[PDB]
Length: 291
Ligand SMILES: O=C(Nc1ncnc2[nH]cnc12)c1cccs1
Image (cartoon, rainbow, N blue to C red; front, side, top):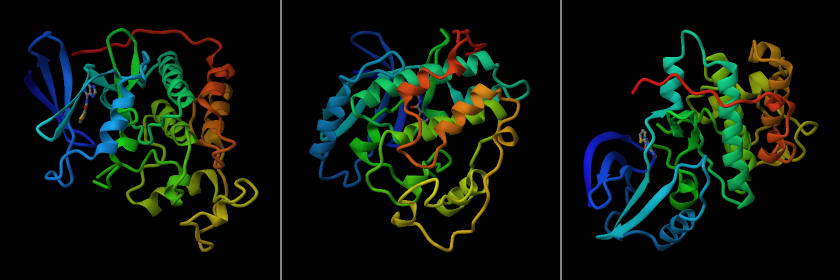
């Protein structure tokens, strides 16, 4: 029922094609979901989880158009967008993305997050490659909720945006994990360099600690009892944000600090972040996009 137009890439869960729906003419992103058994068919809890996502609709969430479970295989049909934030950042490297556009994108992403989180759905794997942009100035979160439905594999899956509680082996993390990832992405928009580009779980942890300080029981009650916490972690002091994300203004640096609080219970929520004075002068610029 779908004509493949071209291969978009290898996604987190399998190959993704730009395709045309033969009975509506709609152009879509068609995602084949890799079965690990392949042979046993689609686990039923995955189908039920994914089916729930068909209802979690918001303008800043890439729309799940259809779920097709046939021949004991799984395909997801998503709304197609022409650019991603990773590609847009690479393109804007000389000049950087203008503040007003960073601000608009951050605000839109926080709306999408606050919607999802109010329904107790997390993303868990936000990263620039899953932040998609249209010609209208919109940015939208892709693959929302797929991590809970299918798992997140090691394969390399980037660790750069992973929250510290996940890295310390917490099993029962919260919506705070997405706020951490979006804070990382905010910082990368501003500086044009990834904030914490680890190449292993411990390198990721120690890059975080080198910037934000090694966490202790003062800033994060309970941290020393986390599964993968080690008393022998090096004890680094915290750096100034003014060093970390120049030339971001005081309001941005305030917001960023709250999004990168170690204690997930103290980390700002998406709802609260929408109220932050950083967004007092937010607008919706139209991006400069060549397709
Ligand atoms: O799926 C990807 N990119 C995508 N590109 C256009 N529209 C999409 N809607 C949902 N995902 C989309 C991937 C990018 C790189 C690998 S897969």
